Image (tube, coloured by chain):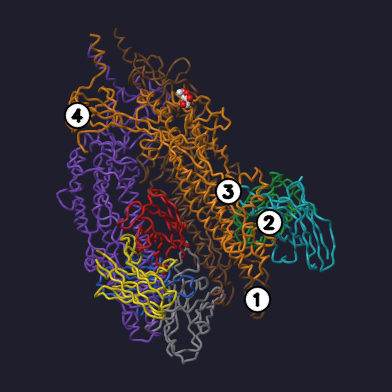
Chain colours: A purple, B orange, C brown, D blue, E red, F green, G yellow, I cyan
Amino acid sequence: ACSNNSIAIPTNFTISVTTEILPVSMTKTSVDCTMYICGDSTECSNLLLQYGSFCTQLNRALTGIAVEQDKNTQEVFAQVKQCYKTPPIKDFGGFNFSQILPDPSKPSKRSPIEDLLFNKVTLADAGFIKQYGDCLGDIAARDLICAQKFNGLTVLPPLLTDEMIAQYTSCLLAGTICSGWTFGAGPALQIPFPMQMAYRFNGIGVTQNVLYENQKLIANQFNSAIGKIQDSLSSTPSALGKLQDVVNQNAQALNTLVKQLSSNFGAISSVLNDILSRLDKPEAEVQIDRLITGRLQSLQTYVTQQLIRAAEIRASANLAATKMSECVLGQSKRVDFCGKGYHLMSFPQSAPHGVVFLHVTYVPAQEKNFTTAPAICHDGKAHFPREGVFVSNGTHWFVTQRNFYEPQIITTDNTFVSGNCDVVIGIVNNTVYDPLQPELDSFK
Amino acid sequence: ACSNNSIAIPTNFTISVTTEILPVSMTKTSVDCTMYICGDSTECSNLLLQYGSFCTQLNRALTGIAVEQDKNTQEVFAQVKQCYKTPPIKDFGGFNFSQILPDPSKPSKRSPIEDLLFNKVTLADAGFIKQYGDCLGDIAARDLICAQKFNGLTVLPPLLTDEMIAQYTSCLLAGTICSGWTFGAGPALQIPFPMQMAYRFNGIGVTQNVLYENQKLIANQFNSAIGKIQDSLSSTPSALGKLQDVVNQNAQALNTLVKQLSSNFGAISSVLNDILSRLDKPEAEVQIDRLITGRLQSLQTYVTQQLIRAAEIRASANLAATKMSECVLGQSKRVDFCGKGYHLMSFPQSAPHGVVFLHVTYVPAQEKNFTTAPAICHDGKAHFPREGVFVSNGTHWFVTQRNFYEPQIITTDNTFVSGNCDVVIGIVNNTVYDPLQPELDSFK
Amino acid sequence: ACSNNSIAIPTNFTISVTTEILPVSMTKTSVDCTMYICGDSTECSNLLLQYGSFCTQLNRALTGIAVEQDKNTQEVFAQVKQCYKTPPIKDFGGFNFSQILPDPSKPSKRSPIEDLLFNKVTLADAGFIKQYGDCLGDIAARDLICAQKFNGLTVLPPLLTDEMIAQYTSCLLAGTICSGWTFGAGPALQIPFPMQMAYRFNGIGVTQNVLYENQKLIANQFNSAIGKIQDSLSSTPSALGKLQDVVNQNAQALNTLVKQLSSNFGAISSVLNDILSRLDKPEAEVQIDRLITGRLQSLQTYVTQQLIRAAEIRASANLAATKMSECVLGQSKRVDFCGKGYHLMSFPQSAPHGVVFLHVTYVPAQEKNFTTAPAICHDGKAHFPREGVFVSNGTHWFVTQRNFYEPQIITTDNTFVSGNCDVVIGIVNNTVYDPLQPELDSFK
Amino acid sequence: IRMTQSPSTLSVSPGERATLSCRASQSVSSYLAWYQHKPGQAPRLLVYGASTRATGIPARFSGSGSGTEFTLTISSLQSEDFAVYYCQQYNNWPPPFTFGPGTKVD
Amino acid sequence: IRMTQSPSTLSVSPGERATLSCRASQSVSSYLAWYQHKPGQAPRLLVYGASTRATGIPARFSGSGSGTEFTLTISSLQSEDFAVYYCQQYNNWPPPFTFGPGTKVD
Amino acid sequence: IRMTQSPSTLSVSPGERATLSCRASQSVSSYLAWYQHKPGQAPRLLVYGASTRATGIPARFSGSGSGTEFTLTISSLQSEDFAVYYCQQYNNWPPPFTFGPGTKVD
Amino acid sequence: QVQLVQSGAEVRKPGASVKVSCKASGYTFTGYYIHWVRQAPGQGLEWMGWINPNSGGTNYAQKFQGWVIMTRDTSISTAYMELSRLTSDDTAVYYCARCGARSYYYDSGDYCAFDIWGQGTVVTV
Amino acid sequence: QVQLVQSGAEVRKPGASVKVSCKASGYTFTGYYIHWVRQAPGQGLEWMGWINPNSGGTNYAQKFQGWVIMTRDTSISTAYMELSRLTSDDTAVYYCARCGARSYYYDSGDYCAFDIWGQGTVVTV
Amino acid sequence: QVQLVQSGAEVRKPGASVKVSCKASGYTFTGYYIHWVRQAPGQGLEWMGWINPNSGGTNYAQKFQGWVIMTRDTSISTAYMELSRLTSDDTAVYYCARCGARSYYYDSGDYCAFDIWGQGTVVTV
Ligand SMILES: *[C@@H]1O[C@H](CO)[C@@H](O)[C@H](O)[C@H]1NC(C)=O
């Protein structure tokens, strides 16, 4: 597919909306050393002194995991600090943002897409997280009372609540749809959305007249894609596979940990005091040491699994953060990085422990090849196009942009003269219309 | 602050000069193992064999700190190797560079700003550094003689002297003020300073005609800012807080180290030989071991404090180096990174153990919103601006650039025809002036 | 060289071809623990249990070296996955690519430059690699039989064969010479090579009319450079110094390793069984332990030398990969990074354990200084150039681009009016030709 | 080194995906293999390495995992897939080649 | 672990900023707290953690530092700020909770 | 620490480049020096450090290498270059300053 | 409303048991660790140990091991500390404090700093 | 064509030598390690050891050290395993397998996984 | 002008003391470490030890510990090395050198390489 006298240019273009889901954080947890090792024991100073080192190491690992998760979510969801109020209007030049812009009427202050994501992503009722949330009672004074039941197992609340994440997402949506984002600082000057889209088309290499002559078509395509994405998310269960899989993995890890907690292993009973009460001290020592070793091994397996999951989530959060930095805050020059085609705009939305990007993609189609000539000779003087290339449809010659087919007649304003026709190789004979000639001839 | 038919553009602009001070290096130091542990002892082979490991580790740490500092200062102050002679002229199109360009008449070959920075940043006379400098005698043969007094405490001279740093800074100033710097290689082709400033304005998104019509105003603003920055530096003592604080911290660390050196701790006397002379060997062993342990602990505290300070200075030097790479050698696209606004130019200057950047900042002001229309219909044919947007001042329509308010009448050369007026949404009825029509009518 | 009323612009330009050779991989090798430590011994379980730890560590190190080499070569030679067929034509607008494009007629499917590189880069016949290749017999079942001869010394075949590397290089050459490469995805739309070169000149800051008026000269220069580079490679032996030096270093390391393998050190004989047969067990234990320690130290020296060489080759491969990413797949904005001047295009070719880049370099020459003026006054109205600067050849004034000397007469289409002549500083008095005036005067 | 498999038995209907987990006390890297041993036939190799399948093994069998934990998955349980699954470690260090406890399927 | 404070006493005029340094033998991370003990009153918590202040504590008190070295600063010394300052370490490892030697102010 | 040189002797014609390798049991960093000892004259310093030459030493002598392996190269062997080459390590740890076995040239 | 109340000053002969009662008001007795510290005349503060009011777990330091017994009474919300074998060096002031000020984020329940203290009981041999 | 053949079931009195013969066909006998495994009734698999048919090197486990003697015959390609001092706990099934499936890239000859096995010999005490 | 001068060749009976004097000229005697090395016939060089002319600190190797006593005379700038218990294996050539060539940057005074040496004294038992 190579030629020395032909050029292939697109004829038609399409606008698509793609959804990219990326997890950003998990459910933080911690274990109490003074209660996991000790348990319901009247005196456990010697046991604590014997077995506190590994417990402290595991607690440090859990603290590192929690701080890494909090740092990741803060980095991915707090890139911009400046903010301003929401736009009351929902339509901008025919584009419908009802599913994206939050609805102030609803007390949740969320979006229909966000509401669907929150409803379709839940947690198992028969889980440790749900029981801990029910027993917490929305008070920090009762944390230890319930932690005694779970032997120090606690769920650390996230640093940023759902309301803060929703507010940040709404502010980002306002800054993207309205006005714009500069490379740094904060929001840019107020500009109408069609003008911003025309600027984006100019950035990707398409003249704004294409948008201005096809505003209705692109608006209809965007509305259809927005309407279809909600149905696709609601119907297809595999769309939200990543977040649901992560939640289920965390829930099953916690469930198997708490199940192994109640296991008696190879002792008379799980009660530490009963072993020493019903047995002599020399035998009770090993009968408790075996239980301690089993619990420590189970906790080590849980913490190494949590470390692996935390590393994976950290990688995913870094990918999400760099995607937001490159595509959300500004136009991205990379091809197929955000969507399949040319990235135009991104509309982030929040989901339980995740972020969804609605990438807008420009896709050329119906590529056609036409004969091209480097220069046109009219009166023994080479003419070169100012911005574009010469394309012949078969009988006539026109000047068109590289990335689109916009046949325009040859005029003295679209071309400039330089040199003679003999020097240039590939010269083609054609007539260059001068608009002054008919006006001067009309006088006669 | 969102609308679908209005656009906000700046009306006025201001030029400011900001000063950014960043430390790049510290005072390197080292300790002699054969003299710190031994001291004024006739025979100390056994003590050296006993206590040389930690001394060697500390010496390696100090060597690493010194090499890191030297690498940092070399990286930050030797980015460009090519050089050429200074410009004898001090005025370039009305801009005054007297305070920036070095004065060949003065033997110091420095600038008034550099002279003020050197004078206002000094070191305490009653310090170890000053005493070592006085005792050195500008000869390397006397280093050991004076190091014996300080028990191996020596001040390593910097790899690059003040003269070399001043020459590099002057060369960078010449390369920035005149000609230019390309992305690599060396100096660019010679070009007048106003033309370079116009190119910078074109880069930031402002037409050069704005500079050419406001050269006097921007020159006066730059001169006023340059004059005021010297008074601000001379009057306000907190401007140079970072360098003075670093110097004072190093001086007080050295002072407390040398004060703890003379401490007798818990022995009869600080003299090692006196302890063994006035006491039997078994008791003298521990009476010397306690002093050795105390000195080793003091040296460990000093070296860990020096390591922390070296890490902080390394971070600061990396920040300074990347700032110089992004802003000094070329225009930076980031907003508010170099100053508060749009970065234009940087004029680095040297200060004792630091670099000061004089960032030039362009700041828009008096933002005003005007009604805008995507296209103008004149004779049933849509017209679109080639470079700019349509702005209405309330009664009449004009074409203006996005980043500035330059009302220009609508003419056939500033707009191009494409399509019909019915397809485009937002068309506005207006008359497009044709310059050929009055010339043709004058004939009749 | 500083002035306020003079600008320096180039007058002539040259096109050069530079060759950059970079190694990408080495000859992977591994050692068998069950045979190196044991050897020709009937029973060696105790010796293996005694001396397997360090052997396992060295096997792990060798495996890491091999996987690093394979990852490096895969990264450097598999950047792009999409591919399409070769262009049958060898001439594109006068440019000759016979030495670059592979010849389908030859069964090797290589290029004359690639054939010369393969022929001039060989390996010593009296080496371990050649003997292992001869003894392998192109079958994996005989690997252990020959490894027994070399005591576990084996040569790991590369993951990518020469055919795959040649195919990837040919595909990259097709994608560069024909059509183009976008920032991501795959090949771009089809475009003639002269048009792509004109686009490259526009990217570097040169109008395409310069290429269109000097196509023959640049084509002749490129052909001459291509013809001369083959003679330079064939004649000068130091051009291929890096690859030959690396190959010789690897060969001599393997040769000295195998020579030390046959050394008897300080025992009766190199045979392990003979030592225990001719001596009692207590003495045979140490007589075999000394041989094991000597061989073990030799293997440690070999593996640490291999680690150093692998680190160096990894650095070189990273440099080659980033050079290919920046220059081969697209235009590079850095100056003197690819060649000495302005980078235009790159044509990678494969060589034994290396990649050669044929960087195309644009070099300006004959720099000349001319008087320049910011603005021109014709009828009491300041005129500014749309794209270019005002240059005086001594008597007359013209408008020329910044990076080249293209004297064009002043016309109303190359300049725009803004403001009055009094405000601007540096105004020059000159006449601006209006093309409409002679046409209107011809009527009278 | 100790190898432990999970679960002990499975009740999977024909034509249904199933999975089996395996783990080790310490890191094993990719030196793990899965073996299928029938009551009346010698054990055969199914997956060697991290995820590479042996010759003659249908694509239904697959392997995944790393570090200390691996998993073996089957797209559809059939009559021929009624045997015991074992984990074999061929890491040179430690010299012993510990096997898996075994897992039954149905 | 050993905790040492500095200096032993201060002579600061009223309405003047003052600082007190504290250090440990080994790394303590952010598990350090500052306690103010009056001669006639029980010690009270002023700053817990690296720089977080306790409830009811005026903004005049502040804390800084990390690793092994911390500092406590007061914007203005007053009559209520005449007590002894102690450093408390609540790191689980080592189990003992070593206190500070104490520092007087005036 | 043990220092070993290579080779034991050389047969190099006048006006020809020659090289000599030196190595240590463990890492030495840049604390290595090359000494030339004539049969009738005291040893003299040629290259101190990694590659720095001593004062009065002609540019023909040069040094290279790092880590544990170093090399000394001569552009042209002359009559004055007929002596024994030794490697000296002045690293403080270990305290002993081990020398090189020696290498003859011709 | 939260307050910790200690018993008054008491004097005991050497080699005798000293019973110090610490009571808490204004908050739930269970769910918060209670620690004891000793301040010697002219010396620093030493952490004697801690008791969990929820379960009853007691952990003492090596120096104070055996000499100190801590009991809890959740019915009246008291923490009774009993010292045995009174030594002449035991003359000091004993304070009871509640471990709080816990960072609800990034931290677990074990790491805490005392926020509320008692009044102080002085014992003389 | 490749196949491993083992001897039939044999019964020996305790404290006696058992000679198990393993034969390989369809490929070259030398150049591939041969290993032996033991499967106990109701227990797992234990790797007894390995023998190199090329040289003759034998490596056994600590538990099976001394009790197992491995000999080779390349003329007829047989790997004889001799057990001595038969114990009542030795009742199991012995399999001989060839170590293969080696990753020709990134791996050496030592690391391999068995791809072809034998038939299995059952011994009863 | 800098030069190191050693004493002439001397012969001593076994089990006697040998006094070797090293003098320095052209530079200040104090402020530069002076080291001693031994070259045996047919063997390598061994660093006997060092002495500081400024203070007087002497450090010897383990092998040469006790046998060697180093004294200084700053008045005439001479370093005296006194041997003891002359053994038949002590026959060698003793050189005195000054440690210099110090990198004034990146390095301290301890790390140095000898730049100027003596003449060499040969002793025979
Ligand atoms: C530049 O500034 C200096 C210092 O204020 C002044 O002396 C000099 O005249 C100025 N140059 C001008 C105004 O051209």
Mark sitting earlier along the chain (4/3): 3
Task: Name the chain under label 2.
Answer: F
* Residue at which label 4 appears: B420
Amino acid tagged 2: Gln
Q: Is I5 placed left or right of E52 in the picture?
A: right
Q: CA distance from mark 2 to mark 3?
A: 35 Å
Amino acid tagged 3: Phe
> Residue C275 has which mark?
1
The location of residue B367, given as percent across then percent down, is 27, 32
Figure check: C27 above or below C404: below
State yes or no: discs 1 and 3 in contact (Cβ < 8 Å): no
Give the mark toward the camera: 4 or 3.
3
Nearer to me, B86 or B280: B280
The quarter of the picture where the C terminus of chain A appears is: top left
* Residue at which label 3 appears: B128
Q: CA distance from mark 1 to mark 2?
A: 39 Å
Q: CA distance from mark 4 to mark 1?
A: 102 Å
Task: Name the chain under label 4.
Answer: B
Amino acid tagged 1: Ile
Q: Quadrant of residue G105?
A: bottom left
Q: CA distance from mark 4 to mark 3?
A: 84 Å
* Residue at which label 2 appears: F88
Figure check: A139 above or below C280: above
Do the residues at discs 4 and 3 belong to one chain? Answer: yes
Q: What secondary structure is found at the residue carrying circle 2?
A: strand
Task: Name the chain under label 3.
Answer: B
